[PDB]
Amino acid sequence: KTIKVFTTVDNTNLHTQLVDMSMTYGQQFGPTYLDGADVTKIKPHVNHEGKTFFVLPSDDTLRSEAFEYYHTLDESFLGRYMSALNHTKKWKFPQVGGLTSIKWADNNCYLSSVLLALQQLEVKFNAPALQEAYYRARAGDAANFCALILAYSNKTVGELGDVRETMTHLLQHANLESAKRVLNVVCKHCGQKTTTLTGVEAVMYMGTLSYDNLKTGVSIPCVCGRDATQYLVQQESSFVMMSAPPAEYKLQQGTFLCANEYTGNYQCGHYTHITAKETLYRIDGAHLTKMSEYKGPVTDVFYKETSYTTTI
Ligand SMILES: C[C@H](c1cccc2ccccc12)N1CCC(C(=O)NCc2cccc(F)c2)CC1
Ligand SMILES: [Zn+2]
C-alpha cells in the first residue's frame, strides 16, 4: 500500500515522502517522531496520510536545512532538543510582573532567570530556531525556547544549572557582531597595557557585580608582582552582564536593569530574579514579591548600555 507523508528537521521545509505499507519508520526514516512520540519503531497507519514527521538529518539536504535553522553541526542536538521538548511542553508559563516566567518544576529556576533577563535586554539571536522560539516565548509560548536553551547548553530537564554558564552558550548565538570592550591593565611598576575584547567577553565579565567598579578599577593578584588594576576605557553594547560568586550585595532602584540571586551552596540552591520597575520586583517562578531595596546573595547583575568612553 502507498501512503503520502511529510518529513522535516526545521518545521519550515516539509518534504513529501512515500512510506512503505509494511516496515516501520526507523528503517525508512531513521529516528522519527510525530508530536514528540518516538514512533521510530512504530508501524505506519493510514490516518497518518497527510501529516508531518520530525526526523534526523539523514541526507545532505536535511543536514543543510538543520544547520541553517539551528546553526549547529552537532548530530546529538536534535534528539536532545526533542527529549527536552517532551517535558518543557508540560511546563507553565505565567505572566509575572509583565514578563513571561516559568512555574517551578524540574529545577528550572535557572531557566526562568535566563528567560526573564533576556526579555529585558536589547538582544536578538542569529540562529532562526532561537529567534523564532524566543518571539513565541515573549508571548507566553516558551516551551520550545526552553527546550532549545537546554539543547544548546548541553543540559537535561531536571538538572540544576548555572545562569552565567547558560548565557555563555546562548550569547554565542546572539547579535554581538558589533560589540566591543576595551580594558586597561595598569600597574604601579610593571607597566601599562591595553586589551580589546569582542564577542561574548565584550558583554560578560566575571569577578564583580558592580559596573561602576569595572569603570573605576578592579583589583587582581598580579603576574609580575603586586597590584594590577583593570579598568574600562570603552564599551560599545546594548547591555553588560556582571557576575561573581554569590555574595551579599545591595540592589537599589535606578542603578541596574535586573539581577539574579542564588541562595544555597554550589551543589544545591535556588535562583530568583530581581527586576527594577516602579519598585523592585522579585520573581520566583510563578511568585512575585515587591520591595524598595534588596540585600542578599546576588550573583549576576545586568545594566543597560549604549556607548561608554572613559574619563581616565
Ligand atoms: C551561581 C552559582 C555559583 C557560581 C559561581 C561560583 C559559586 C561559588 C559558590 C556557590 C555558588 C556559586 N552556581 C549556580 C548553579 C549551580 C549548579 O548548577 N549546581 C548543580 C550541581 C549538581 C551537582 C554537583 C555540582 F557541583 C553542581 C552551580 C553554581
Ligand atoms: Zn603588572
Image: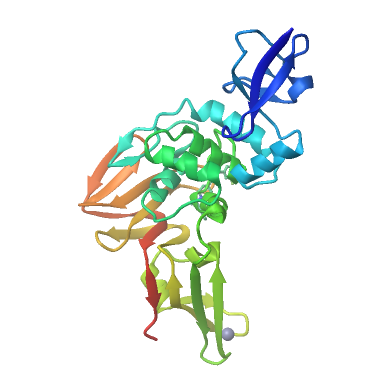
Residue 292 placement (x, y as % from top left): 21, 53
Can residue 43 be seen by looking at this rendering? no
Residue 48, above or below 239: above
Q: Nearer the viewer, residue 286 or 82?
A: 82
Q: In the image, 3: left or right of 163? A: right
Residue placed at 72% from the left, 38% from the top?
61
State ligand 2's quadrant. bottom right
Q: Nearer the viewer, residue 210 or 166?
A: 166
Q: In the image, 10: left or right of 163? A: right
Q: In the image, 85: left or right of 250? A: right
Residue 206, above or below 38: below
Q: Nearer the viewer, residue 217 or 154?
A: 154
Residue placed at 23% from the left, 45% from the top?
290
- Where is residue 67, by image quadrant? top right
Residue 256 placement (x, y as % from top left): 32, 61
Residue 146 placement (x, y as % from top left): 50, 38
Can residue 42 be seen by looking at this rendering? yes
Residue 265, above or below 34: below
Give the colour scheme of this rendering. rainbow
Q: In the image, 170: left or right of 299? A: right
Residue placed at 50% from the left, 76% from the top?
182
Residue placed at 40% from the left, 35% from the top?
102
Residue 42 placement (x, y as % from top left): 70, 13
